[PDB]
Amino acid sequence: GTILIDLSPDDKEFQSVEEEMQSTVREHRDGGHAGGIFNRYNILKIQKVCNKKLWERYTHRRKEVSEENHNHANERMLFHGSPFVNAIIHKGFDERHAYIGGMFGAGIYFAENSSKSNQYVYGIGGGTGCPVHKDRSCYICHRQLLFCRVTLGKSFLQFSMAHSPPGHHSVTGRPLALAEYVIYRGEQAYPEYLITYQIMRPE
Ligand SMILES: N#Cc1ccc2c(c1)[nH]c(=O)n2[C@H]1C[C@H](c2nnc(-c3ccncn3)n2-c2ccccc2Cl)C1
Ligand SMILES: [Zn+2]
Image 1 (cartoon, protein in one colour):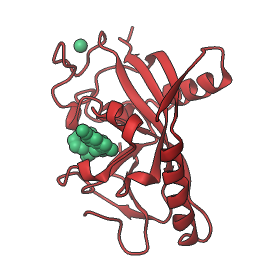
Image 2 (tube, rainbow, N blue to C red; image 1 turned 180 degrees about the horizontal axis):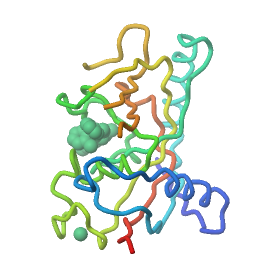
Image 3 (spheres, helix red, strand yellow; image 1 turned 90 degrees about the vertical axis):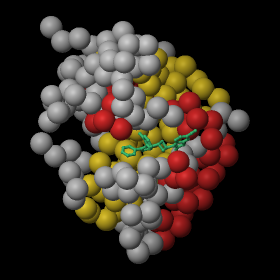
């Protein structure tokens, strides 16, 4: 029951998500090893993701979290990257697929820097890069990120686990140290925008 709405480049909604993507790029510690070398994107397509059931799932969980966090959901708009964006927009996030050996355990990972999430698009550590060229810094192949509504609630701070600690609803990690956000229940995030893009070759 997912509908995708293709947003026009003239749309203020398109532009707002576009700006968030470009402006949150950072120069990574790994020198581009995981996600490639770039300081900007070619943004190709922004699609609003509309799924009533996934939204109801999300708001139902948000109510419970808010009750346990002084009536505040601690909601954030965050990026997600993984090879499984197609599955998520249709079925929602699903912690049953989370990697037990994750830095912060078997959760679903989000970032406030688009470039951080970009590092996970082809897998952990950029995996083996694009399928066609096996190139983690591929400028040719089109990538996709999600820009998601995420309920953090009472977030447990951690440095570099299967559920949040008691009384908490997420983990905020700081492993240059950028923030990463981890949820252990898939219904705490709604995949709001599907972004199709390329990393741009610098010059
Ligand atoms: N088929 C199928 C399928 C596969 C995965 C699904 C999924 C469906 N629905 C999901 O929500 N997922 C999430 C996306 C994936 C994920 N989210 N965050 C991470 C990550 C990020 C950074 N460090 C450590 N783990 N992963 C993940 C989990 C396992 C391998 C690779 C990745 Cl990117 C689990
Ligand atoms: Zn490629």
